Length: 357
Ligand SMILES: [K+]
Ligand SMILES: [K+]
Image 1 (cartoon, rainbow, N blue to C red):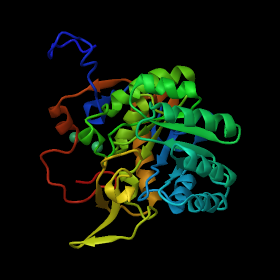
Image 2 (cartoon, rainbow, N blue to C red):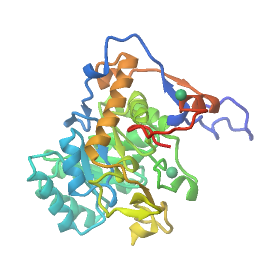
Image 3 (cartoon, protein in one colour):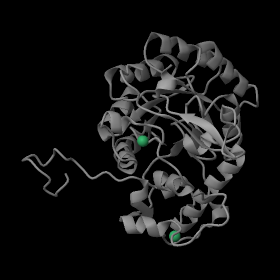
Image 4 (cartoon, rainbow, N blue to C red):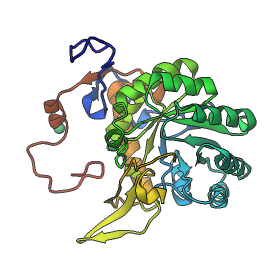
């Protein structure tokens, strides 16, 4: 436990120190890898390996069929959002399936209606069902995962989330999950940690979930909080097998929504699925906000920047594969270390394709 005395007589009350992406850097190591020779393939689930270890979020401002098609063509996968009627979601799965036999996932909730939705998605040819919940360590979520796996698990892979602890990941593994999705609160548009006061910083959440999942051979999906290509490398080094992205993809041409023009600039709508506008869950109050992000152009170019940065990280850490990157070491840093990591003491005059102010 956290050794430092911070009050009371119970040393387990404050149980650990949580780190997130900006708290760590990957240490370079001996290398015979250059970005060109790195292999970025990685398991999405026990049975499915992607060429690029990225998936798009199941949000109504990120992933519909156009995004799912573009993600699969880029070597990743999209998870179709579930904020729409069951027949429309199933229709979108079909749209993706008839664009080349591309991989696709789709989100479902828990309960009878979610069950009907799942069954329809499976009939439509979905490859991955994602049981998409705020708190997967609730007994009802574990049941849903276990039952889908029992009924359709031969035909479809079943992902469960979200979790932020070792015990929750362990419960999902025991329920038969084919992958575990980690992230309680880190999302750019999420307010769970603020309105409920609940969560775990994302690097520690990954390390803890992986401590349960890795020995069981179950891939971890790092969901939320990623803003730069280097964050993907950190998530994967912490032990995740793939990263799920919302904000980084919401600004692309393929994300749903029309372009927003404000003050000579271009934006796209991006909102939490727990935001008032989205709910319109078991929630009594919202756990997200509604906002906008800058327009970033074609998905393909964004993914090229992200995989290029990941490949650089693999070259620096001497990792020929994602499986080796998962063994890399971190150094913890201070606020000055973070300031030093970004550009500092200079005015940027030109935008970089992989770095914005
Ligand atoms: K947040
Ligand atoms: K720097």
